[PDB]
Image (cartoon, rainbow over the protein chains, first blue to last red):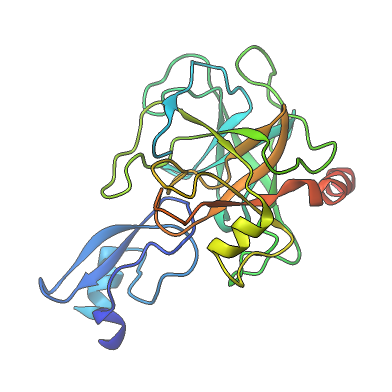
Length: 56
Length: 223
């Protein structure tokens, strides 16, 4: 749903190691990243399928 | 752990790995059936792995137990990270021995200048990702509350304490949350948050466990 999909990926300040997916706007595709468990932002989806389904 | 050393095997026998398919947070064994960790490490299926040294090789020493109850503190605040602590009740008691043991809860709140040992399998680089196979260790001090407040102005509550080096170069990192900070043989802190990993003037802040000893004790009792 686009505004979410332009935000830069963010780990946040917490120190857990959760693999998440974010949409990358230059490359037009969901890429994986590591999320720390708190904070961060909306470009943070649990799967590739759900990420491309929102932003692709 | 950025800037630490590999722990001698089975020297941190109370260190556990919380696992859901992959390692995502650490924890501490405080008796045969309960594990303490950070509340932001909540998931609904958690498997606790005890006796681990190399997290990617079956070594023969390990015990794998599923989490039967996960209880976060009632006042955990997901925005400020105030009261970031949770208890896990294992489905069965573990078998205690040379490489799987308990750590003592605090007798009192350790003063500034105490040396602590922080351990974990979290990322080892400040820029980039490198997940160690083997448990890392770090010797660091508790900072004066003032230094801690001055580094994170307005965001430190009475339930938080900072450990580290204001010069940067060493510090816990992603994958280390929930892990033990033991000072003088007592569990004084739980790895929680910081900005970046090992960046100057951004030390590690931990949940101050000495403020929760009656909560832990009463929660074990009630269930």
